[PDB]
Length: 229
Ligand SMILES: [Cl-]
Ligand SMILES: [Cl-]
Ligand SMILES: [Cl-]
Image (cartoon, rainbow, N blue to C red; front, side):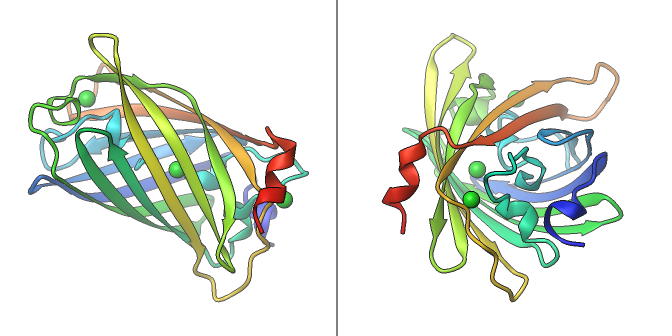
């Protein structure tokens, strides 16, 4: 059983995230549900106190294997199993700071566990990330291309809405690498439409978020694959 055969829904998730921003250390944990392909949630919470950054900015650090892929594009993230992959991210909040994340995953009993680290340095203490002045991030198309002999690269530019109704940009660039000592067939260049919706659980007493991601792959520009060898 491998690949898409291993991703029979419903499934669940867990996360453990160790972080630091501008010298402030913190941790997050969470559990989530994946009812069906492409719709995946996460209820996460800060276990060290209040989160020292925006929940909106931490949303992309908080599971591409749950994306919904049509049959005509390779689902690289799912094809990495068994064996797994790592994700390495850089998120530049333009005019403000840069963070990086590293993710490792394992799959057991229908649950994907993420163990992630986050490092963020140089942020403005009156910026929106540290003052928690974001409301949401807008939906976006992540561009996925073959990268090196055995990985992929994911790139996006994200619009973050502040409380005053204006936008800040985050430039995001990620590399995914199979860690399974085996060759995984690269997909053609394509796009991943992604939306994040966040809310609060009225009862939960912790600093937390309840997040859903909807992620659907498509060959949005059929000529694009020709540019990536
Ligand atoms: Cl927030
Ligand atoms: Cl990404
Ligand atoms: Cl493909």
